[PDB]
Length: 87
Image (cartoon, rainbow, N blue to C red; front, top):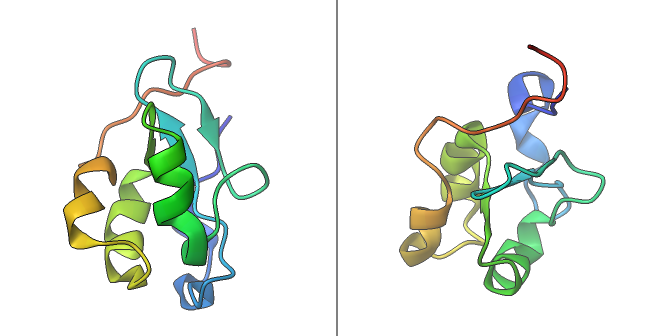
């Protein structure tokens, strides 16, 4: 029950892509629907201190050019919490 970029053409990061964000505390994960847009990630992030960007989006967003390297700290390193349907 998640939305990974394993099948999302990373070329659409021209500012329109919907970068998925995962909450650090509760693990709230949001693919692109409710997630922030590449060209606004820095705004949405600054607005959501409890949220971060998905692991594969840490690298993608990193290259995004829209997010500042100083914000890469919230881009995650790899692991994230997302269940709903497992145990």
